[PDB]
Amino acid sequence: PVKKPKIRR
Amino acid sequence: GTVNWSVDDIVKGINSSNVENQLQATQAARKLLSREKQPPIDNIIRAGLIPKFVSFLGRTDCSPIQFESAWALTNIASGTSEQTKAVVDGGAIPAFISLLASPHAHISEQAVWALGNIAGDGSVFRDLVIKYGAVDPLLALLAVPDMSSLACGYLRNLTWTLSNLCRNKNPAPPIDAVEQILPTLVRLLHHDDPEVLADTCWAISYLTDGPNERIGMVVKTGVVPQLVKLLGASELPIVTPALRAIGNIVTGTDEQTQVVIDAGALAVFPSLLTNPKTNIQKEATWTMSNITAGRQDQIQQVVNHGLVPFLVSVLSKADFKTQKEAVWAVTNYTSGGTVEQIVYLVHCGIIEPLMNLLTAKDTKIILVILDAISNIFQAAEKLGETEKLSIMIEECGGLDKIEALQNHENESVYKASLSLIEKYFS
Image (cartoon, rainbow over all chains, first blue to last red; front, side, top):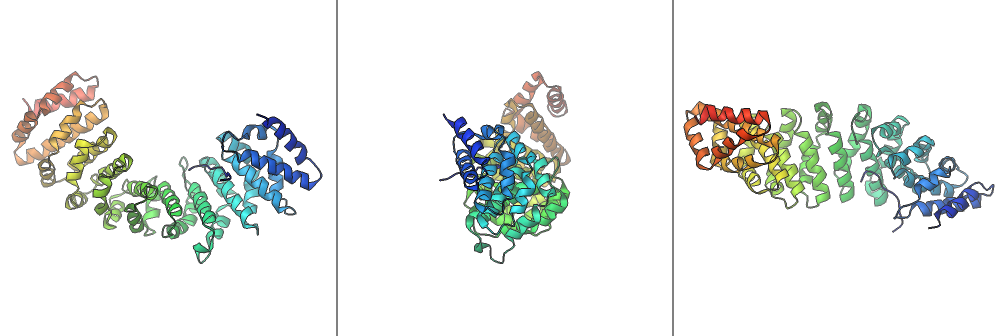
């Protein structure tokens, strides 16, 4: 994807 | 919904002269911003926190707050263009580039991720990331003898960020940056991780989406045979961008298209043209159409690989968006092909499914079909068989459909159909 947040599982 | 009070507490904590309080506040911001559902990005921006976060990126005395701030800013930058812009305007880009050299891999890689989101916004922020010097240190993180020495997550995140540095047009990425990055992409295309392979294919699809000079840079690396290998992969996330890259290359020169043919691409097209993903079928038919726009020897390779019956079948049976690509493949074939090639095309049964699309409610496609019919009659003329062709078209109801177009709204359609009737059906 173009942008992506970092999230926990 | 108590986010506003959480944000107020974060502001208070982040302004504490006690670094443990500041760290806890940044932790709390990172937690809010890593919520899956509607993270409160605008609240955090409006609270004036971005300058504080950017300052914390530089706090070498407290690696945990560098980490938390880097993650918080990563997720703000993952948002809308306005949200990404707030991060950029806060001076984040050079701070993140400095963090690429952190001795802490989790911090370096968080910086990689943030820069990928910033560059991913578009060409303007992409170029700022390049201008501030991101490429060299990103490539250095990948310049290890064994790529398997890097955690899978890290290598995937580096590859993805590199792919965003290759993305977008108006303008395309600076040539010197592409020259720096390309050899690493070529290396990565031989990796065994499917996500790395997918994003590396995407990167190459971006670089080949442009003028022939840009396509030429990619072709000259010798990577096309490996792309063709990946074209035959079973993983759709790899085939999709590999096929886009190959399709992009054959929008280039005849010589560039020949590289694709010499690499054995055509042998993969029976599978691609019948692939259950209509998107794969469509893109494969598009690709075929730009190959049949080539030289007569290139058309002949399409013939020799048994692909014309596949093109007839797609024209006959596929979804309309794919049928549109097949019409183009036919018209290009008939525009550039020899009389013998065109005779073979008719023998494969092109006329009836072509005629059947003259009822389509797409004016452009009607015009392309009428071009193809004109082209086929020109071959018939050289053979002295225009009458035989006109009878064939009458006998499958094709002339009725051409006659019907004299009632079409579009003047070019009216004139084109009238011309065929006057020349060959009078």
